[PDB]
Amino acid sequence: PEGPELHLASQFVNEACRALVFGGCVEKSSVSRNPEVPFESSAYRISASARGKELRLILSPLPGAQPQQEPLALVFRFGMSGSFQLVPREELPRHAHLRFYTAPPGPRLALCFVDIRRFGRWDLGGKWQPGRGPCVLQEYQQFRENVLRNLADKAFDRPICEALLDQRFFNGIGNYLRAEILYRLKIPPFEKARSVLEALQNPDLLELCHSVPKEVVQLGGKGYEEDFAAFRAWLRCYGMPGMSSLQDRHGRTIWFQGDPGPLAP
DNA sequence: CGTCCAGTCTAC
DNA sequence: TAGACCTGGACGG
C-alpha cells in the first residue's frame, strides 16, 4: 500500500464507522509484536486521517462513557500488506492483528487491522513519524517546498527512482507510483535526482508526485476485485508488457520505457 | 514438491 | 550495503 491506499483506508474507516458505536477493549492477536493498546470505553467512535504512508485512528469516548477516558490516537504503517476491514465479529479474517468491537444495539461487528505479512507497525502516541516529509496528497505546497529547500541533501545524489522512495521527501510514494510518475514525463529512472529537481525551482515532476496519486484516489476502491480491475487498467507502466525493468541499489524493481539513465547498473 | 515474487527497519 | 522481517500466490519439474 502507498499513499492512495492509506488515504482510501482512512476514508473507509470514516464512512464505515460514521454511524457505529464501539465499546470494550482493543484486542490484539497473540502473534503480533506491536504494542497492546491500553484503551477501554463502554461507548466510543472511531475516525481516521492519512498522511503519506501513515494513517491515524482517533478513539473518541461518548459523553458519559465509563471508564473515564481521554480520546486516544494510534498511528499505523501498513508495510506490504496492511488494510482495514469491517467484518461480522465471529467472521474475523486470518491475520486480523488488531480489533475494535461495536457495542449493541444492532449486529456485532469488528473493525480489524489485517496484515498477512506483519510488516505493518503501530505506535501508541498519535504522532506522525519524526522525519517523514509532508503528505504528497494533502500537504502538496509544504511537500514541494521541503524538496526544493533541501536539494543539497546526499539523498538527491542518488537516482531519481531511488530518491522518490525516500519518505523524508516523498511521503506516500512507493514502487508503483515512482514507475507511473517517471513514465508520464519520460524521465530515465537512473537520471540523478538533483539534476531533475535543480532543473525545476506541462506539469513538472513534483506536481505529478501529487496529481498521479490523486488519480488513484479518484478511481476509488481496493477493498475500500472489480475495483482492482479499474486500477490494473489505469496503470501505464508498472508491471506492463513492453516495459523495461531494472533493480535499484536496494533490490526494488523500477519499471520504465526507454533510456535506463546515466546512473544505471 | 520447489523457486520466485510482491516497505520499512536495523545490525554490520 | 545486506539481510531480516512474513505469508501466500504463480509458476516450474
Image (cartoon, coloured by chain):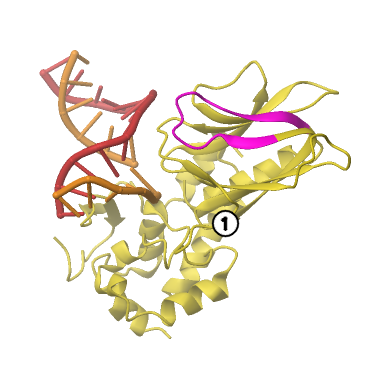
Chain colours: A yellow, B orange, C red
Identify the secondary structure beneath mark 1: loop
> Residue A76 vs residue A196: left or right?
right
Which residue type does callout 1 highlight? Lys
Residue A174 in percent (x, y) is at 40, 54
Q: Which residues are magenta?
A: A22-39
From the viewer's perspective, is A55 left or right of A33? right
Disc 1 designates what residue? Answer: A127
- Determine if residue A220 is in view: no
Q: Is residue A211 visible?
A: yes
- Mark 1 Cα-neighbour bin, 10 Å: few <14, some 14–19, many ≥20: few
Picture quarter with the C terminus of chain A: bottom left
Position above or below: A136 against A45: below
As drawn, the residue found furthest toward the right would be A64
Give residue A95's position: percent from left, percent from top: 49, 26
Is A26 part of what is drawn in magenta? Answer: yes
Quarter of the view holding residue A193: bottom left
Q: From what the image shows, is residue A168 above or below residue A91?
A: below
Q: Nearer the viewer, residue A188 or A40?
A: A40
Please determine whether, in this image, residue A151 is positioned above or below residue A78.
Answer: below
Rendering coords of residue A247 (x, y %): 21, 52
Is residue A50 shown left or right of residue A265? right
| Residue A118 part of the magenta segment | no
- Above or below, comparing residue A22 to residue A90 in the picture: below
| Image location (x, y in percent) of residue A156 | 30, 73
